[PDB]
Length: 30
Image 1 (cartoon, helix red, strand yellow):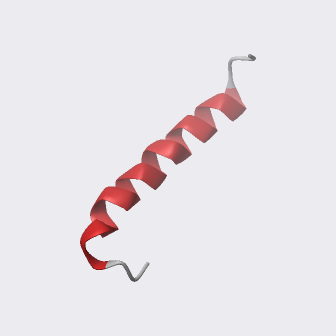
Image 2 (tube, rainbow, N blue to C red):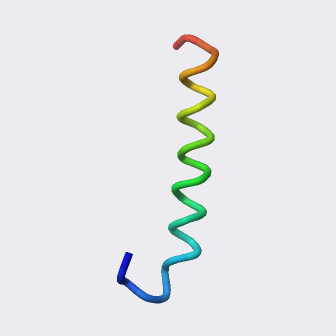
């Protein structure tokens, strides 16, 4: 990532998005 002020907030967005992916993969069918 090169856009300077947003790096930590984005890393947060990815980690929580990732956590959602793991959970939606592992259990609970929609």
